[PDB]
Image (cartoon, coloured by chain):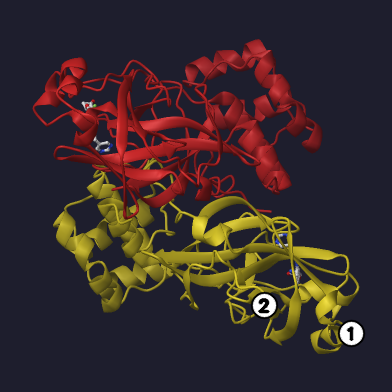
Chain colours: A yellow, B red
Amino acid sequence: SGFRKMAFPSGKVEGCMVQVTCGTTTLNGLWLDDVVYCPRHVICTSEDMLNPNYEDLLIRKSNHNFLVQAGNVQLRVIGHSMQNCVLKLKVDTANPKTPKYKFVRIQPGQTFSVLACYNGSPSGVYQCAMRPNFTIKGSFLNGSCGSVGFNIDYDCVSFCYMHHMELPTGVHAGTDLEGNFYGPFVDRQTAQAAGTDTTITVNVLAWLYAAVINGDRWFLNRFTTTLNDFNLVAMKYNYEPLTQDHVDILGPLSAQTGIAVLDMCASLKELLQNGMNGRTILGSALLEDEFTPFDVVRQCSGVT
Amino acid sequence: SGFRKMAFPSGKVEGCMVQVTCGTTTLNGLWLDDVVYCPRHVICTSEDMLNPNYEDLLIRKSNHNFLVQAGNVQLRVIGHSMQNCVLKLKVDTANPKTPKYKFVRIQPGQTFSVLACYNGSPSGVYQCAMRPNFTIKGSFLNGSCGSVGFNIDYDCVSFCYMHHMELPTGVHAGTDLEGNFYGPFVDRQTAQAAGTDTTITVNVLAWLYAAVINGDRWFLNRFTTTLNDFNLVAMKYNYEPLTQDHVDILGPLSAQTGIAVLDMCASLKELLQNGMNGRTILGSALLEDEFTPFDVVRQCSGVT
Ligand SMILES: O=C(Cc1cncnc1)Nc1cc(F)cc(O[C@H]2CC(=O)N2)c1
Ligand SMILES: O=C(Cc1cncnc1)Nc1cc(F)cc(O[C@H]2CC(=O)N2)c1
């Protein structure tokens, strides 16, 4: 029993973190096979960042200008390329600690673990969700650029996120491992707004199922609702509309608890309209939306 | 910016996890040098657990009865001993992945990372606090026994906790790496109550400093208080009394924010007496006590 915001064990990803320096700028790189991936703004100076012409900036850089350090060993750069907003530095040595890996572009509402790094060294690991507005509510400081987000499927690491920037909002923006930003963000030092963020409804329901599995049943009621009626309430409270696909994904949790999805929706409706009245669910005074139905099943079944 | 319940990178500890089987029971072991540490209740059957005589039970076990598996390789047991509530199985091979380590017995209120494991394999990592009542509010299932709690100081892992049991309360109890339980708990299948748990006052204040550092300043007020007056309020709300030692430990955060500790105490007093009025602090609708002042400094400064 118990329910925590759990991250994947980070060992496979720690063995991939390197330091990349270009001029005066130092950030984190991801070394997989003979390629080091990092945010392309490593080639910029503070004045370049206001309106950078990355193609012209990269043209003034040669293989010897990129310094790559793995722990205390210097890697030799033999190739360099820009793919969207990431640089691919070809090194002469394949990473002996390269785990089985994939590059995946996650969907908003999906979750992942972040290994926050500084100077090629890991400092901590935490669980995140890609928000519907394509930002992440992480914990990142100056020097954290190049830190990656991932998931693990038994032995295979699926890299999904590379950290690039913080919006003045305090929220974080970044790319997939092909350098494509999630959202409308650009790697330029200019005011950028993350659109309106919504609450991931399917995740809150999954967490209400995790609460029931853990003994927290006070919010359960004698009511039911319909997809259309619950959706009228979801739009009022900035909640993503619930679809039959979401209902299907909640199937294993509905079967495990014996509570039909539409009955769980009616508990959520009353929680939205009436608040929590000073009570808590899984040690929380608000409705949690950063646990997917897969996360709930995995945590409640002990998948290693 | 941003503030998350951050765990230490778990790679150094994943390289130490093994599976220990004794009869029908399988649990997790910690392999460091030529010794595998695990909870002593691995030698028990469900009937033995009601009132176990560990000394007599262990007498019926020989080195060959303990099966130790590291990934897919079988370790050879050449010695066995019981130290309080843990078994020390001497193996013929030293763990090549043994990091620099210490065994420390943490104080209540201090924090640590848990690498939850099943069958010698890690499933996730999360941050915990040792509660004033010596329990931890973890996420553990059957098979998770032997999972460890630790801290990392640059390259040195300080093992502080080994998971042994769950109380019917849903909270978790365990030992230090010498097998001494934190709290009054015994490794017997009998009703055990964790005493009254208090809120770690110094940690809530540290988190209020992390909130100020992150832009959340709504709770700051035009009031001040004294240690004695604030303590009258702390006892009313099941909060640990604040001492001058706690005030001193908050010194770096007080210097960084420019807000004197007694002024932060007055904000906490008004938050206790008036609640949050539907507002949040660092994305939370309740007062968080599982971040020490060291955790706040480390997260807000990027210590790797
Ligand atoms: O934020 C960091 C660096 C950093 C600091 N703190 C946390 N995480 C990252 N760099 C950065 C990189 C970049 F290509 C664009 C950019 O634009 C600003 C304007 C806007 O909004 N974002 C900022
Ligand atoms: O709880 C688990 C096994 C476990 C299950 N779920 C989460 N974490 C651990 N074993 C266990 C071991 C033990 F030596 C004593 C004992 O007494 C019960 C009575 C009381 O309270 N605790 C239980």
Q: Which numbered tag is attached to residue A185?
A: 2
Q: Nearer the viewer, residue A92 or A235?
A: A92
Q: Which three-letter amino acid code belongs to the residue tagged 1? A: Arg
Q: Residue at x 59, y 14 (%)?
A: B231
Please give the count of numbered marks on the rendered protein.
2
Q: Nearer the viewer, residue A33 or A18?
A: A33
Task: Locate the N terminus of chain B by quadrant.
Answer: bottom right
Q: Position of residue B287 (x, y in %)?
A: 53, 36
Mark nearer the N terminus (2 vs 1) = 1
**Residue B51 found in image quarter:** top left
Side of B163 where A171 appears, left or right:
right
Residue under pointer 1 = A60
> Eyeballing the image, is A143 above or below B85?
below
Quick check: is the Cβ at mark 2 less than 8 Å away from ligand 1? yes
Subunit of label 1 = A
Residue most extreme to the left: B47
- Element carrying mark 2: loop
Q: Nearer the viewer, residue B135 or B303?
A: B303
Q: Position of residue B204 (x, y in %)?
A: 58, 31
The crowding category of the residue bearing disc 2, from other C-alpha atoms within 10 Å (few below 14, some 14 to 19, many at least 20), is many
Q: Quadrant of ligand 1?
A: bottom right
